[PDB]
Length: 46
Ligand SMILES: [Zn+2]
Image (cartoon, rainbow, N blue to C red; front, side, top):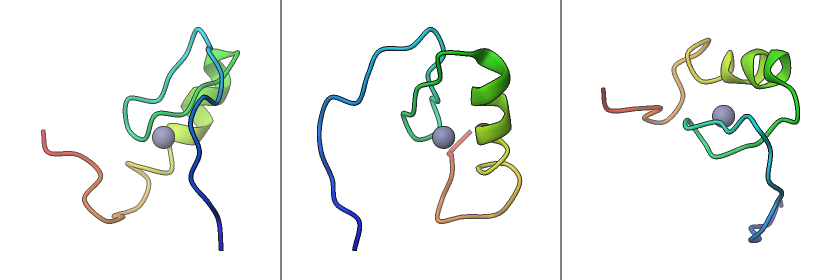
């Protein structure tokens, strides 16, 4: 089972959804499609 750790890396594009980081925008965009794309466990409030 996956684990949890701190300090992943600083990138010019962070995912306010989960907290991920992508050196490039195009990337963060393809990832965010996972939050709005489906209906996970409470993605966001507003
Ligand atoms: Zn995310």
